[PDB]
Amino acid sequence: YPIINFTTAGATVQSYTNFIRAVRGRLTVLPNCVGLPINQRFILVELSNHAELSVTLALNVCNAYVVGYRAGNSAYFFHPDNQEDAEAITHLFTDVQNRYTFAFGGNYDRLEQLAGIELGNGPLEEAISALYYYSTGGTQLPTLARSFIICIQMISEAARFQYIEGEM
Image (cartoon, rainbow, N blue to C red; front, side, top):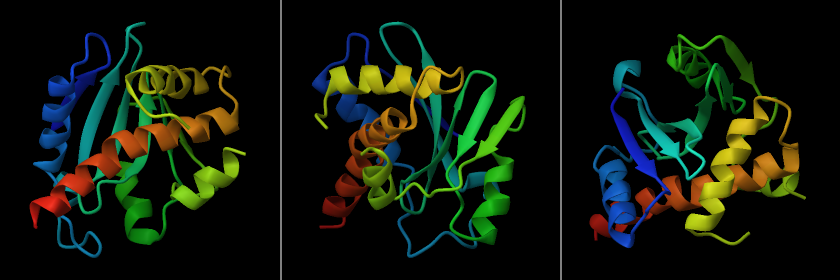
């Protein structure tokens, strides 16, 4: 899948804006993804911060939302909303050693619930480490949730919004 890169290290309003445009440039907002070959159903967003930690988010091209991610040798996926997506996510991060699918979904209402939230470069920097260390036992679920929310609002939601105002 196409890979968009972004780092919080030396981040500018400009580097961030181009990042979002890039994402938006690959969306195909439709009621739900179907007809799209799984080959191009997702965008991969590689995020890295000042500690040089990197995680890769898998975004659904139809609605821009995060369906899962990769941190090093492990991958995590939100409980798919149905069977098509269930089988779809099996195509993501295939060379990864550890695969896990959460029992809960990745909608805002669930994440808010699990979280028990300032946005910005600072919070994203920290959200990236949280996502990374989750895979080694250093991140508690509530923090993981708050971190997903930060990634989702600053990336998924930002691209959707611009896509829409783009359609006037």
